[PDB]
Image (cartoon, rainbow, N blue to C red):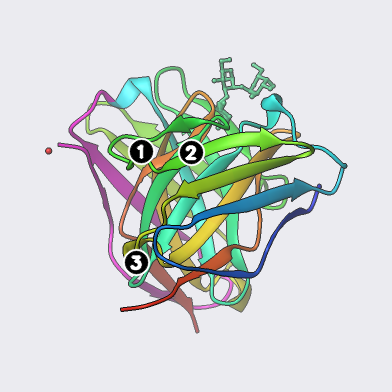
Amino acid sequence: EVQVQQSGTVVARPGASVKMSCKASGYTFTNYWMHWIKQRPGQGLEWIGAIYPGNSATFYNHKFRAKTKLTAVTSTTTAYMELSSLTSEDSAVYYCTRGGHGYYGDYWGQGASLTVS
Amino acid sequence: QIVVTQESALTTSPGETVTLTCRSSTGTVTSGNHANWVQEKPDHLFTGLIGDTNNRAPGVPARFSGSLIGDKAALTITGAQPEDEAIYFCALWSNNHWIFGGGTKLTVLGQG
Ligand SMILES: CO[C@H]1O[C@H](CO)[C@@H](O)[C@H](O[C@H]2O[C@H](C)[C@H](O)C[C@H]2O)[C@@H]1O[C@H]1O[C@H](CO)[C@H](O)[C@H](O)[C@H]1O
């Protein structure tokens, strides 16, 4: 049942803006948080932010706040992350994960790779 | 904000109990930090293991348990199996951020 399906690979140029998405299926979208995790080889993992589709509440990592916008569309059970001002530091694999009270990711999407070049 | 620290690498044998720890640079990990543990398998395969310090995620084997031991959050694997060979990441909720440890690579000896 539970599926978090992410959009595909993105190649973009420095200074551009990209929007990535995660479609959730197999659970009620408005009873869970959707978190976004960045994995950069070597660097390990970094949390970007989270949105609760039930009332649109968001938490952002202070590092990413200006450059990230998180949204969700409940009719399509899809969450979006828009990143702007891309630099080479943004090249990484991005994951959507399902969270709730006390946890950020019981189910993880497959990862979407972003290369800025 | 805080720095979260884990052992870089541990080796165990099949059938042994192994414990992995997770520390906060503030000196102690509390229940309010909701310590989370996830497993990374080859090919970017991530499985959520433990949330809110000791709650096993859906479908996780009973040999995995989480708790607070002393000043640290801990993941204990009672009776390690070869399939437990993986990287384990701890994350703590601190000042409204999830902050990740660097991961512990666990080596296990031997061969809808
Ligand atoms: C509205 O969301 C806050 O409150 C609910 C109900 O208590 C918590 O479940 C929320 O915490 C979860 O979601 C965030 C994004 C993290 O993944 C941690 C999860 O437990 C969230 O709690 C935060 O906000 C409240 C204020 O409302 C407090 O600051 C609390 O310390 C935070 O955890």
- Image position of A108 (left or right of B8): left
For the residues labelled 1 and 2, say whether their Cβ atoms are less than 8 Å apart.
yes
Q: Residue at x 68, y 25 (%)?
A: B31
In the image, A99 versus A85, the foreground residue is A99
- According to the picture, the residue beneath numbered tag 1 turns out to be B62
> How far is mark 3 from mark 2, CA to CA?
17 Å
Residue that sits furthest to the bottom in the current view? A117
Please, what is the three-letter code of the amino acid marked with disc 3? Pro
- According to the picture, the residue beneath numbered tag 3 turns out to be B82
Q: Does mark 1 have its CB less than 8 Å from ligand 1?
A: no
Q: Earlier in the sequence, mark 1 or mark 3?
A: 1
Instruction: Provide the residue span drawn in magenta.
Output: A1-28
> Which quadrant of the rendered structure holds the N terminus of chain A?
top left
- Image position of A115 (left or right of B101): left
Callout 2 crowding tier (Cα within 10 Å): few <14, some 14–19, many ≥20: many
In the image, A86 versus A78, the foreground residue is A78
Where A39 falls versus B24 (above or below)? Answer: below
For the residues labelled 1 and 3, say whether their Cβ atoms are less than 8 Å apart.
no
Please, what is the three-letter code of the amino acid marked with disc 1? Ala
User: Is residue A69 visible to us here?
Assistant: yes
Which image quadrant is residue A8 in? bottom left
**Disc 2: host chain:** B
| x and y, in percent, of residue A17 in the image | 50, 62
Are the residues under badges 1 and 3 in a single subunit?
A: yes
- According to the picture, the residue beneath numbered tag 2 turns out to be B65
- Image position of B41 (left or right of B104): left
In the image, B108 versus A76, the foreground residue is B108
- Image position of B16 (left or right of B99): left
Q: Residue at x 57, y 60 (%)?
A: A45
| x and y, in percent, of residue A48 in the image | 58, 49
Secondary structure type for disc 2? strand
